[PDB]
Length: 53
Length: 50
Image: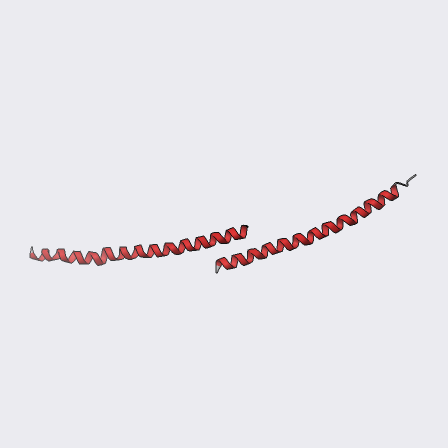
């Protein structure tokens, strides 16, 4: 029982590094990569619009 | 790099259409004046036919 009372404190740290931290890193990646996709599409839109006018 | 390139080449396409349009207008105008001289001379000669 004492061994598993320490297994709790274990998983609480392992899960932070295995489950939480990478999901949080993925969120930051997705956000700053989305700004780049948007930036390229607005610049491309302006180019196509200028080419038409 | 994609934007500046597309814009520069779109201006080239527009410059070509404008230059060709102006050259064409000068030819159409000149050709009309020459053709009108045919019609006038042909008429001034035909009007005298017996």
